[PDB]
Length: 13
Image 1 (cartoon, rainbow, N blue to C red):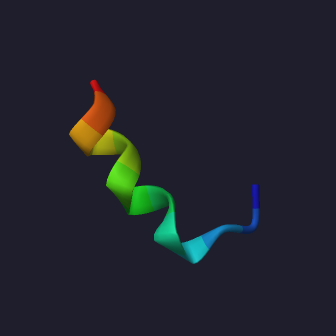
Image 2 (image 1 turned 180 degrees about the vertical axis):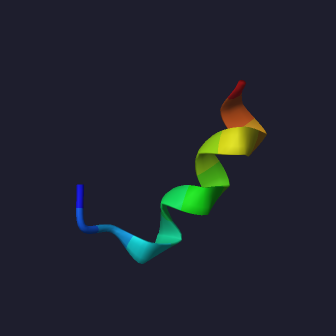
């Protein structure tokens, strides 16, 4: 995963 906006995952768990 080379996504920089992956930090938003914490908002779904």
